[PDB]
Amino acid sequence: LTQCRPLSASMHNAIKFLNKEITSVGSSKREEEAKSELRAAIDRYVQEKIVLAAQAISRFAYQKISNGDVILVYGCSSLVSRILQEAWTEGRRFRVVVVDSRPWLEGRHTLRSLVHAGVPASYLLIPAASYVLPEVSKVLLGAHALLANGSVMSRVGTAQLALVARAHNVPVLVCCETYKFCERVQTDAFVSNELDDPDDLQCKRGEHVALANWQNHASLRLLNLVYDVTPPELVDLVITELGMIPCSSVPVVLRVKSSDQ
Amino acid sequence: MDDKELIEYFKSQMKEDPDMASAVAAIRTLLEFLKRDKGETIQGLRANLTSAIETLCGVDSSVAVSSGGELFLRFISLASLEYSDYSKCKKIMIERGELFLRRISLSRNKIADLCHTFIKDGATILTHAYSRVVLRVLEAAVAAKKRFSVYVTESQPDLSGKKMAKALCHLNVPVTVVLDAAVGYIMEKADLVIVGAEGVVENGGIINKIGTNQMAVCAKAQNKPFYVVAESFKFVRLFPLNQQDVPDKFKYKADTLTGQDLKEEHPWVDYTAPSLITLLFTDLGVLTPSAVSDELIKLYL
Image (cartoon, rainbow over the protein chains, first blue to last red):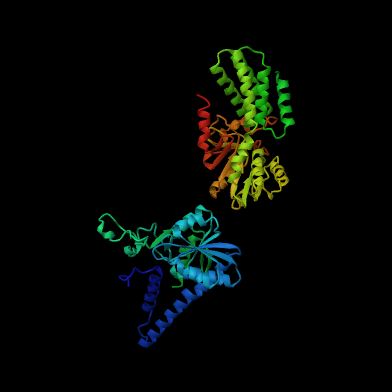
């Protein structure tokens, strides 16, 4: 699986949990009983770490969203989309600005959902973020991982949006389930990252295609970065199933989730 | 003119036109002193004018009066450099002084015309203390069919903020008075900050009513623009390095001049560094702070 694609933080944590569960199986247990217990454990893990966690995070984030707000979201995040949809359903009225970036253009996904729920939505690319942030009252980001030092490991451009929002005096909130918290630490996006397919950087502008046969130029390199790291000083709040916590409370939460195990 | 008559003339000039600035009135009094002078030499006239400037600064301790006096001294020096004969020098001095008064009587209109276009429609403006130049700028903005809200600090201990609020209410502008301590609480609402200046120091910073420095610091913290409106005669050749480097004669009022209810004789002015200032709206146009020093470097030398 790592060869097919580098594992996400959630996948790593799930693998660690499953290995711990398997190791703690008594040798006297029958094979079918152990297999049924393992399947039940995996089902409980999915139900508690993802579904109930998402519901609790949505309930917590409902308090921050206010009437007349303009919330800026980035890319595609199921947790953020669920939070916005459940806030709209419960009676809050607000606008959402979807910031998207090449080459994945995952933000379009979010856009579609925000129209199915009836939420008014603007859409623009990341370079235009500085133009739209004067209107924005809150930035709501999803995180692929929260590191032990408080850094937010997310889709590339998340730290950019956090920086520009800080420059525009706009609060930044991060939504993450505690099952995605990690004990690793990163100080930059260079030490650990994923390099996607460089060919995805090719674009169709006009009849010509720049960067076509880019490998023919010996000095030309395409850098399709996937992740980036937001330092904790650029994040104002983290909403988890345990509530609203500062960005520096990641190491303690891990501890609380480790004393049990 | 004797000292008593000089003081009476300055006070009467201030009283007849309440909107007249202190520096302008001081310059007009200095021109009257030049007209009434009896000496027939440049050095005697310079000494008499220096004594008159000292008298006026004793009457009024604002930086504007001192800067106006220094400007008049430089003006007579420039007139004397070209012309060796004292009679023609005095005639040209009188004519150019009348022209100078006529020109600097229109500084506020130019400042308002240049600055009113920087106020976005539907914006909030934060202001410290009372300032006639800011009032004129807001008048021009209102006359241009712009709707905006104003927050004004109380500006203790003279409470000039309430006077500014009443003046703005006369113009039918939504104006709200806040405490000084609340400035950091309210900066997140203000789109921009507009303050006057009692003097523009060499580096481009300003010396203004106490509380302006912390307003500028809070604005810099939240990345809000900080705009200063000040006429050219308020330019001074001073270079303070910190708050204690400002001369004591400016901090403490004319009539004003331990460890137990001392209060250390609360200062009336503080210094705001040029790094906290976005732009200046002078009668010479819209300037960066670094331009201010230029206007002085070319003025002398």
